[PDB]
Image 1 (cartoon, rainbow, N blue to C red):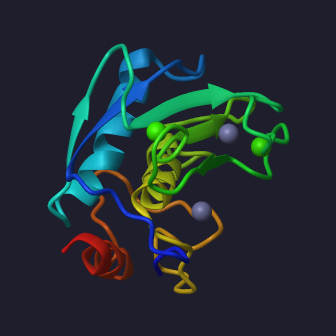
Image 2 (cartoon, protein in one colour; image 1 turned 180 degrees about the vertical axis):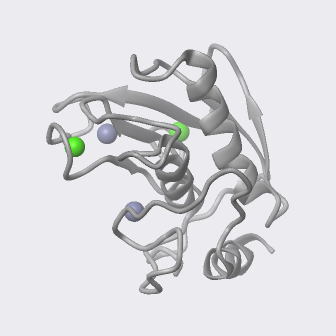
Image 3 (tube, helix red, strand yellow; image 1 turned 120 degrees about the vertical axis):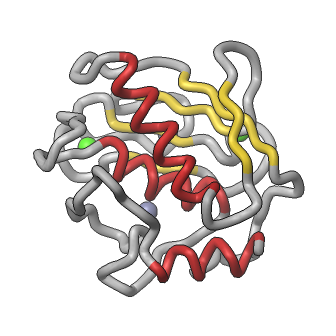
Length: 163
Ligand SMILES: [Ca+2]
Ligand SMILES: [Ca+2]
Ligand SMILES: [Zn+2]
Ligand SMILES: [Zn+2]
């Protein structure tokens, strides 16, 4: 499902920056979750993601609580977990995570890798899917992560935008 107006990135080598972290995972564990979330999309498209440690990146990633400057506030534990902006300059592409969640790398609610993988779909121009097996389904569901691969519906979706 592709977003109304089909916003898409014009370049396929995009940068990202992790602006801050969550105390419930090590910094390394957050960096891995994020790296692997991008790689899912990279191996199904021509997109190549490059991390930068400082300065201005295409996709900023941050953990924030409640009001955090973009007029879409987070809501405390549970409920909304994260959100992401469609491709564009500035805030476009960026992905925010609710700092008040329990973030994990386990089956326990909420696996950061899974949530980030979903948000980056939005960052790249995908909408929600109605397929309950799709990563882009609106509601979180745990799936095994140790050798995770994009569900077929999400491959279909990114290929429709980027080939
Ligand atoms: Ca951006
Ligand atoms: Ca929340
Ligand atoms: Zn936000
Ligand atoms: Zn979503």
